Image (cartoon, rainbow over all chains, first blue to last red; front, side):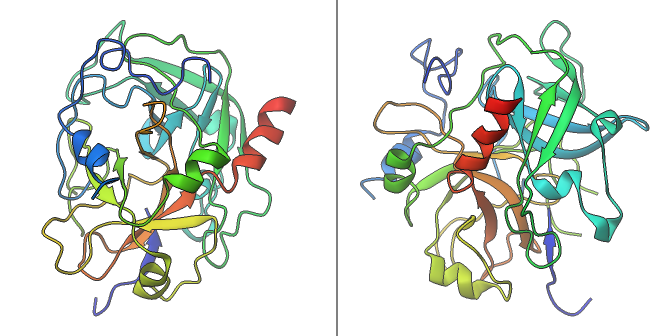
Length: 9
Length: 29
Length: 251
């Protein structure tokens, strides 16, 4: 929503 | 190594895909 | 695959698709490393956070496919799994470390024209190739942007390797030697990146030595997709090279 969160693909 | 990584419809047919040179180039570059 | 070409028939003949048995579903990507074994991302098979805990019988794979908006009979195959093998020390808790897994097929696919196994890195290669600036090829049927976006034909793309300190910083996740990261930097001319659904797919390089394709990494994860200032990470296939055999020798 207001960032960039690390996540698996 | 046997026969891995050698694309039949390419390296076996002496055909380069439309992109590899770019890589083959990034060794010098 | 974000910002990337469309494949040439039989380009990544060691390409594999990871399917949820029932309901038949597209989950992840994979590579064929012989007629009996398939590589992949550990998280595709096991990711508690999205309650994911598959077993041999929950899945099946398709090998040698180019387009989904079709079904090339006598071309593509669809094997079944005889046993999955997730890396013991795989860390799904902290940083998806060692994110790697092998899958055995109930019955060994036959290498055709469009189905060939890719090669694995040897200390010698990996040491010389896997350097910052060199390039590798990422393939998959993942998202075409960051948010649906579903392609009909295998998306290819070529990305250079980034230095460890850039990655080590471009993220706030502790990256280990079991991972490297690639992609263009802020202000580089081009873009491109893997994205959801690409994970577990290959990342080959073409050896200027023997002139063969070598999967050096496995799509592991990333923050968003293609966002400038951010680079996708891959499993350092060679690192865990060890594990990979201890598993095949045994069976």
